[PDB]
Length: 120
Length: 117
Length: 119
Image (cartoon, rainbow over all chains, first blue to last red; front, top):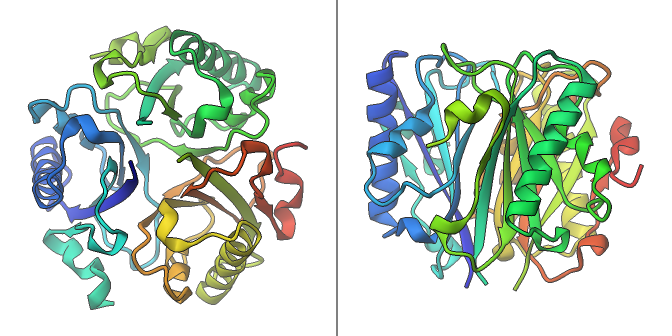
């Protein structure tokens, strides 16, 4: 019974509640599908946002996910790095999975494609 | 065994070390008691605070729990969300437990009772 | 099999990329060596920095570690505590290890040496 962190990153086009929730939802949906994540196997989720996002906690998006009511989630501010990607939401989901470490599916969407390791 | 995150949240009325530590201690005490948490089964603890809290690291409250000296804890700044609860301290404790996900008892105290689902 | 957080802390003399990366690398190297950490056993890593560090994400230092390219890592902002250490980088590495809680070797370097828990 092993555990793995699963990362995701995305961006919003503006700091509005609809955009923050929709983009966070889309990122979570991709993490969940690609890693076949059962909510009952999720230890916890962390979600960071850059300090230019104030409209809504990205964690509220989890309310839209059937079966995820009891998955603990909390947020944190991301560092403000010169040249860092603006309006960026990052997920670190801790899942009970037996997949080999190198075979975990980390997800980069929207402008956060630019953070994908192979593009560095 | 399985592992589970346990959430808590509380608030203080002012940014003082006494209030931050007292309220953080009371929140941790409730998490620990209601979930029968032994320190050796705690992987780690994260504690966030809103950016109106500068008085003390909430992690210092662990000094009041005998046997918790070596439980790793680190802090982080919570997002500043318009309309979000002010002076708010949030805990995420990761614990070895076979308790079913829906039976883990998360704890919301003080003005953070408004945050409970 | 048990899981344990391993903490570290260090400081930088200036907010410049190569200083931040080298200090973070040195802290990670010490955590890894002293705890004999196999990357494949690491669930995830968090690295925080105080609000006076803007030059680079400390997490970029992990790219310098052969064998660690699949370890997930992300950053966050540390609280700004009056009397807290300035220019401070902190690590929380979550490792699958059966080592007893009191035997884990948490690492405190540079100006952060007095932050160790039992002090």
